[PDB]
Amino acid sequence: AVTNEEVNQMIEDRKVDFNQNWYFKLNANSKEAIKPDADVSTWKKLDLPYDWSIFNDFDHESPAQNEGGQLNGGEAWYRKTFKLDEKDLKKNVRLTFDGVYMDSQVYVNGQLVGHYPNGYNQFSYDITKYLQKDGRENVIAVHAVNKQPSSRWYSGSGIYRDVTLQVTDKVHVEKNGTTILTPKLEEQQHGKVETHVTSKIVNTDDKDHELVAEYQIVERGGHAVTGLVRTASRTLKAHESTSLDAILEVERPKLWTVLNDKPALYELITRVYRDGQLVDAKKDLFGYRYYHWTPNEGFSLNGERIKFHGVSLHHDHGALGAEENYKAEYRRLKQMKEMGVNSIRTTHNPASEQTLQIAAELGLLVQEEAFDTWYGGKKPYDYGRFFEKDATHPEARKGEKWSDFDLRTMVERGKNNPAIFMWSIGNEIGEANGDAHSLATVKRLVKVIKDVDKTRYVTMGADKFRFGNGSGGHEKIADELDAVGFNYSEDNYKALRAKHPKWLIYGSETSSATRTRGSYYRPERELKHSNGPERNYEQSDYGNDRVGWGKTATASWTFDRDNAGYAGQFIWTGTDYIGEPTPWHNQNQTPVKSSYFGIVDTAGIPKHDFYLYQSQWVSVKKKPMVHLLPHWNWENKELASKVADSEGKIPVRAYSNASSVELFLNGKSLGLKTFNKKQTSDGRTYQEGANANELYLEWKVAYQPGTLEAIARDESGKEIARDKITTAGKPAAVRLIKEDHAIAADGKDLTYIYYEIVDSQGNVVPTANNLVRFQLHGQGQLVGVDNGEQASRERYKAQADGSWIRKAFNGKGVAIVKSTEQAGKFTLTAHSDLLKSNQVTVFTGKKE
Ligand SMILES: OC[C@H]1CNC[C@@H](O)[C@H]1O
């Protein structure tokens, strides 16, 4: 008899991590790459993922230009050899790539399996017929090409996401074969909820077989919530496929939501029987949630009205480059969640598996975006050139173009993930102008999605709405969407809303405020696209710089807050990313190589607007807070002259979700100030400062060195939070700050250790740029160093002599250390010239 234990083992064994033991060579000879018994002594042995570009030096002559981060691409081969276990000799074998950038070719045993242009969409190949008989070694060779320029942001190059192997019986649930629907959830939620499941089953055998599917639903990390539900036994013919169906009932399921930080998730277990023998078993993640959206009230989730407090995110992880990593993406998404973010937009490409899983786990709604261009292109070597070409993937359907195939497979991949609620079929598509070609195209793409999944809003992000009054032919394209995304179009919302009263409208992309951490300039002014030499390649952490087409955090948020019919926004961006260093865009001889748009810097350190947003989006009951800016080191006349008002006072500002804030300088009160409480036209309560354009409270403070302390209080006058800033003396030491006391010894988990330049009393020196040198000992591996400074041209990776160094920027930076597969510990030591050295130790071992 097959025990539940055996079924769970079968599920685990069905899919394996195939990232280990690859060989990499830039510009490798094609014939050596694909052939048996190649000499790999000149190749780099490594474990995936591996983005080769992040290891380059910045290049002012890079064909990527600074928009692409001035890190070159080129072409490379990755090669791996493997053998099937004796028991797996007759099994079906599928190889899945979560992302390869880009224009890839996969070879198995000297033969071309497929060519796949898309740099971000997951793709997979059934490689069974290509493998050797009798368990002799197989060779996989992957060619990746990044011919530049191909991108408006840093892409990275190569196999930058996971590769997995599925080994299954000849009769099996096909790739993305599971559909899970809860069509009557709202009505049924207080009793038995019908859960409609569908399995696409394939018989790859040359014999007919009798087929039965058996299902059970379980709480993820919890218990069973159904028994086994069985389909009627039927024949599945040789080389044929079929869809089996069942309905399971789950009583009073916990509903997945963004309103908590560990939302409920479930798994469907599928057991497949061939002639009465269990041959295939798998699980599929899903959740129970429903939502609704109306023109005038916007969005609701499980009956609760919310706004999308969203961010747009690019894929890179700073010093990790394009390398996707669960722990890195977890840190980032949890950080967005700590801010009050409840949703994300994967701008402008399919998401990794890690991103999608973590969003489901943390409770973040997701818009996953297929395209940055259609047939027009934006950069010569981007996806545009492939968009209407015939798809040559071995599993593409007749007549499918690449755009059809890529969009379909993205949707089929993610259709059960409860976090995804929107599919975007394009961002700022210039050619989508309402002409016959673009109109045909929008309807074709909408239909590709609706044939797979009707439960999610098909959308686009459109900046065309910001020009003039926002009207034009593009309106016909918007009419074909479930929901219309406005990029930077607040100014035309009122008119577009009166014109199109049935549209579901939201800000697909907003703000594009530009900021450098710890840099301050002219807080009394709003600065528009201010990029003169007097700026020193920095933007203001007061949040008063924004691009020509952009808005400040305050202006973009207050508009959203005031308008119920504008359902939310996805801020450009939640974090900085490599490339696009507007407002120095493609000024290639300047130092800049990474973005200013992020609320948080590339090193994972929040800029001040993080706390502005937190004060707006996180309830005083959940996390009472107060945050002061700027720093309190104003000895430097040049720095101070750019900040001080006419009376020479420093504008000190507090963001807080409390009722009042009282500022003290060296223990002396500078006066309690109280937020003005107000209501939106539809009765929503909010707080503001001295006027509608100020969400902070402000004091003009005559500079006296010492301590500024802010006391935040509830309406009854009880202290609920404080913040404080202290004038630092001269650098005296480097201090290391551990995020984790321990991590898993799985060779995948990692940790972020911050370094700070401190004075002799342990105050961070807010202007310090001292060079820090790092040593690592023990069971760890340094994998990155960063300080988030846009103008920096420092390496993120090891120097050419193997050493690891990085300057502080405005007192701070981070070092990233990955675990090995051995338990133990690692010690990070930091040194700096004439300063005291410091070390921390992080343990490695058991997960959880
Ligand atoms: O302000 C910069 C943004 C404009 N909208 C599209 C984004 O990818 C980015 O270029």
Image (tube, helix red, strand yellow):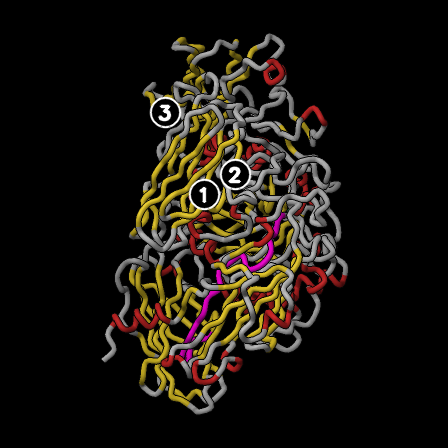
The boundaries of the magenta stretch are 154-174
Whether ligand 1 has any atom under 8 Å from the Cβ at mark 2 is answered as no
Q: Is residue 167 above or below residue 211?
A: above
Q: Earlier in the sequence, mark 1 or mark 3?
A: 3
Assign the N terminus to one quadrant of the image: bottom left
For the residues labelled 3 and 2, say whether their Cβ atoms are less than 8 Å apart: no
| Depth order, front residue of 654/766 | 766
Amino acid type, mark 2: Asp
Question: Label 3 neighbourhood size at 10 Å, few (<14), some (14-19), many (20+)?
Answer: many
| Depth order, front residue of 301/24 | 24
Q: Nearer the viewer, mark 1 or mark 3?
A: 1
For the residues labelled 1 and 2, say whether their Cβ atoms are less than 8 Å apart: yes
Residue at the extreme bottom: 207
Amino acid type, mark 1: Ile
- Residue 160 is covered by the magenta coloring: yes
| Depth order, front residue of 129/182 | 129
Q: Position of residue 538 (x, y in %)?
A: 63, 29
* Number of callouts: 3
Residue at (32, 45) in percent of width and height: 825
Q: Kindly report the distance in space between the C-alpha atoms of the residues bearing marks 1 and 2.
A: 9 Å
Relative side of 740 to 782, left or right: left
Amino acid type, mark 3: Ala
Q: Is residue 17 above or below residue 343?
A: below
Q: Which residue is mark 3?
A: 721
Q: Which residue is mark 2?
A: 786
Q: Position of residue 604 (x, y in %)?
A: 48, 39
Q: Which residue is mark 1?
A: 816
- Residue 72 is covered by the magenta coloring: no
Q: Earlier in the sequence, mark 1 or mark 2?
A: 2
Relative side of 792 to 685, left or right: right
